[PDB]
Length: 8
Length: 220
Length: 217
Image (cartoon, rainbow over all chains, first blue to last red; front, top):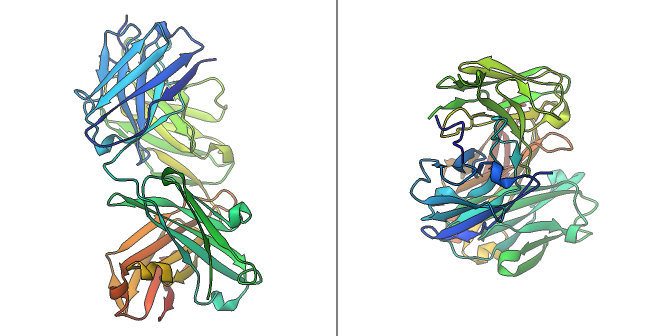
């Protein structure tokens, strides 16, 4: 599971 | 090829709930995050929610947070959005779009859309009114007639003139909603040689309430 | 939120023209980890989903024609179509994809230029059908005109009428690029029954005076 690149 | 196919949109009364589905073919579903983007009646696009590829990070548009919930079932290649306490401002066409995990480039894969409508209105069947003139533009070359479909719910109606025969010089203006009811209007412009000799009929089927009405544009 | 501003709202174009449309974002979209500005241009044609055109402010997706160019940095990003062709007419949206929430601009709509054309105004009494069922909608269609801008005024026995008016406008027709609109004024059998002379008055570019259309009863 990986975060969204837009989750800054 | 990548495919995303939405299901679940329907007419919901405000406050209720609906649950949408999107079905992913032609990629390793499991490797990619997914989002639901909404297309409002006012034509605006709105991001609604994102879920990461494993399911343990879920991002929500602040107006949706609390009420909607995005799930996915990596086993059945399906993404979901359970939606509760639907405000009228939630109606729209909902698109699942793939999230570009490796390319970080935006929404390159979109689905087709499922339409969510939210209103407490009741299914009302239209009144089709024939709109015939007083005189053509000086009894001249053409005569423009119209048909008025007042007060129906829900959308749509299909209006044709003379069963489908007459398709040139028609204008069907979009429907406008006014206190739970719609109104639509269509014009047809035919040469004065045609009407009244030829009967021009306006036919309106409102599938949603089992209404098929046919109106002859009668002068007298 | 990053607020994305797309000016203008509409662009009138003819094919082979160079067009340019703006997108401003309230915060820079520069993602320091990829060194890219995270802005994506999309366009959408009626019925269809958006289609991704340029991402990272200037990189062109594959399959997107050579004519789309994107550029800018920080807060001002712009899209250019150097030889707009007729199949480019759609609404163009820019999107922040740098940080959550993802925000889309309002859209810039492309429309085609053609010659001015003034409206064929036509007015209609209530139908008996209607007039029996308690109400009266006097309809007035104003068809096939260009530009988009038309203004329509109702007047019952010489005075202007505000309320009771529902208007609806077509989008630019594909055959001839001309708009149309209906204005319908609803009143009661009774309210209509105590007045004569109904007028529908259009005011359009192509004229200094109103196109006035009336009926008496």
